[PDB]
Image 1 (spheres, rainbow, N blue to C red):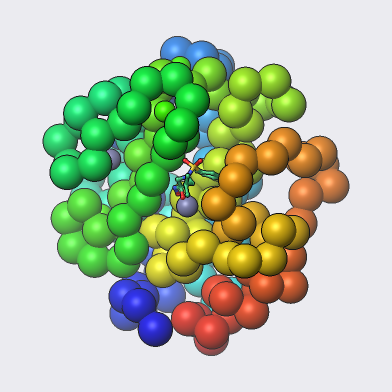
Image 2 (cartoon, rainbow, N blue to C red):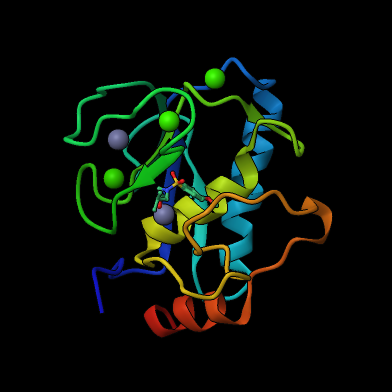
Length: 159
Ligand SMILES: COc1ccc(S(=O)(=O)N(CC(=O)NO)CC(C)C)cc1
Ligand SMILES: [Ca+2]
Ligand SMILES: [Ca+2]
Ligand SMILES: [Ca+2]
Ligand SMILES: [Zn+2]
Ligand SMILES: [Zn+2]
């Protein structure tokens, strides 16, 4: 298997906030996305508002300091680094997308669930029902659930 966090208590911090959405709505989407993974593993996530965190959540555009520049509107929506120090774990969202609560634009929550999967050590799935399948598709958020493949994947890494 690939890198995993060698601890079950994992911190995150939101570096900055997209202007596409209300700040409260970003906080909510991210909290909910971590909860999805916490709900099927022994992992515990703690939000920090200031200081050192394992997973940094970042909205940025174009070339943004890592060796993986974003590409404008469309195309690549987001990327994340697997567990490790520094940029390890970090989840980056392309600000040239239009981030949403809803079905229009790109849903932050669903994209974050995907991204968070990578920040925890998952790669892509070949199951089209899996949140880790590498195509963005809106599905009703109130009824969203991880597929059986996603749960096998993450439980193979933790627990
Ligand atoms: C559900 O969340 C996803 C997040 C990003 C992608 S992506 O289109 O930006 N993409 C990069 C991605 O894997 N980063 O995590 C797939 C790529 C194979 C085109 C698609 C779905
Ligand atoms: Ca990190
Ligand atoms: Ca893009
Ligand atoms: Ca935007
Ligand atoms: Zn990046
Ligand atoms: Zn991905």
